[PDB]
Length: 330
Image 1 (cartoon, rainbow, N blue to C red):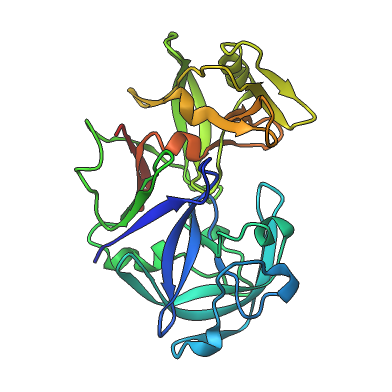
Image 2 (cartoon, rainbow, N blue to C red):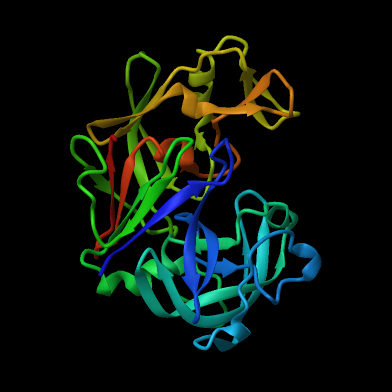
């Protein structure tokens, strides 16, 4: 089997991407944030504290003839950005782009943090990291991909995120029309439950490539590119007037600037992030200070190849017995 679904930016900055997901019978379609940095499929629901729902579409398990309470199961998750959610668990039929999993754990939120409430466009998350990170207790549950894997034509999914435009998540096949040149594959460590890999270096603009190992995670659920402070300083030094602002919470730059590109290495291959991908716009409405899309990972404890990086590539998440990651230009 295969599936193919379009993923759409939630706003004009590509702050996140939503993908429609069918849950239950008859289908209830929710727009979920596909997150290769976590491993829970959780949704706003009829069980979510009413004051914490503000415009989201909810899953109502009582209206699904295939929903079953997973007795005794609870979940609770905290994300790298400080947000969180928790609740109980149903199993139900879940379909993405024509690919159907029966008995998928659907984690129903009883509580969500303010960041989730305030974002009316995201109805939940669909985790695509390794199932070892799944938070369901006392019986850990599998991701949608893990459940689908054996049925897929090939045990893979691909992320093709757009810049200020829709893109695609495919399951079970590689669309050879969706990228240019070849896909370069690189080793993955699953030790921390992430799609963790090592970039071979970087360049800023038309500058020389610096060969240096940068361990990090391919994370579709993180907006920005978080790299070591040395790398980030080298980038922003090429933008007149750019500075790290403790008050704002990262590097800012004059909105009048033209940003240089940023290149990262994948083996001997190179992925180029155009400068415009690194612009996250005014820090507040009407400001001439703009927020940068490359930020320091210092104090995160891990480097994160988030959407800023991934949207410059066609990315293969290869879930074979020994997982790997592939990157192609597009």
